[PDB]
């Protein structure tokens, strides 16, 4: 509360570390469904159903331009990518499996880097 603070966690490396994680996600072989924004002109249903589209290139641009206030807002956008994928794609499809794999990969790197 006012004038009463928990000890200061060092957050000075967070930007660099989120960039490294994001690089590792960009270079995974199963990243191809998530590299670029879904083409809303060419994919029926996507625009109406998926209220907040998100992709790795959009996260990279937000990261590079100071649009994440803290590492939790970064993780929320990464998770959004996989939550959107599960909303629109069957589990038993190439894209559906890709999303599960990438979410697993992400959550391990997140834990190992920060928890």
Image (tube, rainbow, N blue to C red):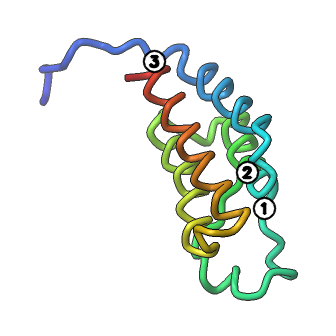
Mark 1 against mark 3, which lies toward the viewer?
1
Quadrant, the C terminus = top left
Please, is residue 26 above or below residue 99 in the view? above
Label 2 sits on a secondary structure element that is helix
Residue neighbourhood size for the residue with mark 1, other residues' Cα within 10 Å, grouped as few (<14), some (14–19), many (≥20): few
Please, is residue 92 above or below residue 82 in the view? below
The residue where tag 3 is placed is 11
**Where residue 3 sits in the image (x, y, percent)?**
14, 20
Q: Is residue 13 left or right of residue 114?
A: right
Please, is residue 19 above or below residue 53 in the view? above
Label 3 sits on a secondary structure element that is loop
Residue 67 or residue 73, whichever sits in front: 73
The residue where tag 1 is placed is 37
The residue where tag 2 is placed is 58
Task: Measure the alpha-carbon separation of dots 2 and 3.
Answer: 23 Å
Task: Measure the alpha-carbon separation of dots 1 and 2.
Answer: 7 Å
Residue, x 80% and y 81% (percent of image)? Answer: 43
């Amino acid at each position: 509360s006012m004038s009463v603070k928990k000890p200061k966690r060092d957050d000075s490396k967070d930007l660099a570390l989120c960039s490294m994680i994001l690089t590792e996600m960009e270079t995974h072989e199963d990243a191809w469904p998530f590299l670029l924004p879904v083409n809303l002109k060419l994919v029926p249903g996507y625009k109406k159903v998926i209220k907040k589209p998100m992709d790795f290139s959009t996260i990279r641009e937000k990261l590079s331009s100071g649009q994440y206030p803290n590492l939790e807002t970064f993780a929320l956008d990464v998770r959004l990518v996989f939550d959107n994928c599960e909303t629109f794609n069957e589990d038993d499809s190439d894209i559906g499996r890709a999303g599960h794999n990438m979410r697993k990969y992400f959550e391990k790197k997140w834990t190992d880097t920060f928890k």
